[PDB]
Image 1: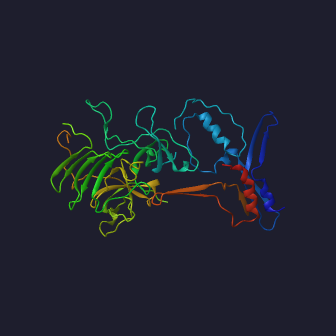
Image 2 (image 1 turned 180 degrees about the vertical axis):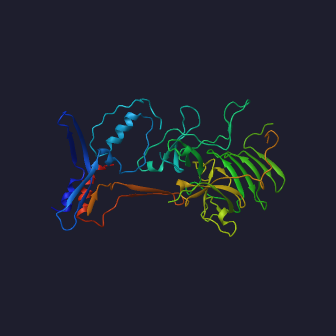
Image 3 (image 1 turned 120 degrees about the vertical axis):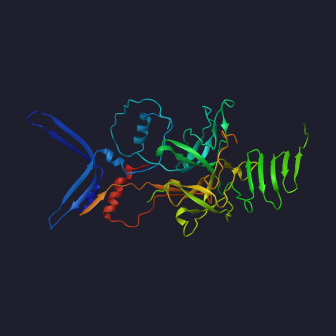
Length: 102
Length: 154
Length: 102
Length: 51
């Protein structure tokens, strides 16, 4: 196949569903891929390891400087999530609704 | 929690809405794109009050827009900035005189209070403005001169 | 990378070759053998320029050789020293008058 | 064993010089050593960091 063609799955979606047959319960998870390993020993055909997790993992690779003047936690969260290229579903609903000067 | 150390900035605004002598600065990471901070305190060599002086007892010299300042953070918290002092640099300084013989205090209109330590000439104290009112204490000659362009009243 | 905190020194020179009000100091680890630093800035309670005062506006009192000063470091970098203020001590001062009246 | 990851190339640095009264600025750069794996990794991580 070629390792550099396998490396094209970086950042793609992953689904995991677990089902209990006796009761009918379920558990679901959605995530993204961030690292890929291509391995092989003793001349076999090889295998692949996919690593990743929740989309907040890809929000941890960009240290910077910035500041916010006279806003609340609602507006600051929206501004931060609007400047990233990661697509995510959000429920924005904090309890402290007052203005923070700096 | 992060830890912060002193930085350099530029004074932007002076008109504090709460009348407490605070200023607004602009940091170096805001230089290319623009921006400014909130109101922060300026520290002084002397400040307080008394019974005969209710407010503004001490040394009151608030910075002007365009000044280069040093900003510090109290308790190491980057959310608690304050101004510690001002700096002289290439764009606004002519340095010290020969043998460091001049010590002065000047405002933006041109008011001056000056001490000259050169005992081989120009030794004394001067208080004057740009219009031409002078009071000069001359130490080489032991004289006192008072000069007014228009009128001197006693 | 190391982190530096304020410390004391002694002034040795005023004669700045670039005419900018800088001084040279001697640290406490240079006392027994000898040595100096490079030229450093001194901070002031008031310093600027104006339209009528082109240069040297504010409070201009440059320290003299033999003075005891406190040295700070910008961003914590030990390669960025500056003078923050001068000190009164035993060899220097007669103190305050009675009731601090002078 | 060959591995690839996602990293950000949208960065810059600044400096203020008071002795010369100048502001210096530098942004990003150009690659000089790359493989076929490096090109696929940087093409995948480009849309993640637009700021």
